[PDB]
Structure formats: C-alpha cells, structure tokens
Length: 98
Length: 98
Image 1 (tube, rainbow over the protein chains, first blue to last red):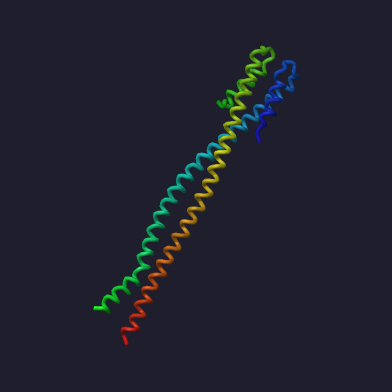
Image 2: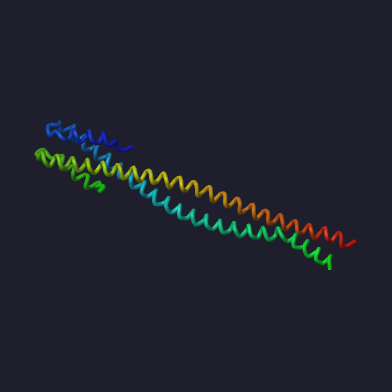
C-alpha cells in the first residue's frame, strides 16, 4: 500500500537539508513520485468501484420494491383461493336449510 | 486538492534545483505535506464509505433472496389450494353419482 503519513513525513524531513547528498535526494524524490502515482491510481479505482456500487444499490432497492409488490399480489390470490371451499360450504348449508 | 500527479511532479522538479532558496524549499515541502495529509483522509473516508455500501448491498441481496423465496412459497401454496378445490369436486362427484 501507500506510504503511511509518518514515512512520507520522514522523506520530507530528509529533503529539508540542502546538503543532502544528490543520490539520496533523487532517490527520495522518486519515492514520493512512485508513491503518489500509485496512490492516485488506487484512489481513482476506488472511486470507480464506489460509483458502480451505488448503481447496484439503487437497482437492488428497485427490484426489492418489485418483489414486495409481487409478493403482496400472490398472498392475496392465495387467501382468496383458500376461502373458496368455505364459501361453497356456506352456500351448501343455506341451500340445505331452505 | 488533491494535487494532480503533474502538479505533484512540478513540486518535485522545484526540489531538484541546487540553488533552491530556503523559503521556497520550505513552502514546497509544506505543499506536499498538506496535500498528502488531505489526500490520505479523503482516501480513508472513501474506503470507509465503500465498506458501508458493500454491507448495504449484501443485505439487500439477502432481502431480495428472502422475498423471492416467499414469492415461490405463495405461488406453491396457491397451486396446492387449486388442487384441493379439484379434489373437492371429485369427492362431490362420487357422492352425486350414486
């Protein structure tokens, strides 16, 4: 992963001294450079991933709404059908009593 | 902010200067330091936000899975009731036809 804030800071402290040997300076600059390039790339991928997750979420919430409505319909069709025999039995007894 | 890679790079090039004046050296390092601290925080927020969304997705997934199960069970029970109505007619036929 990317440099911890304290490792980044330590590199800046090194660069503070103008008497730092040239090879140490250009090594430190390259370290900052590679780190930042990677960090930015990783951040941009995370942003792309986060956007796609937000679409997934909206879609799942809409599908969930659909199923909830679909479920309610089926439960209604079911409770209607469950009473048909009882409705028949009622009519049978009314007929028998007349 | 956060600095673009090429804006970051330009500060790295300033720090590659022999005769860089102390006050410019100091300002350039503070720019890197301030930028990195900010970037790290932004990145950590986005990481945490992403984790939150990934949990929300997993949950919506399960809730959808549950709805679809209950849907199939209500449809199954509807078919079971229709079968019962058919058996009722069959029993009635057996009694009528005597």
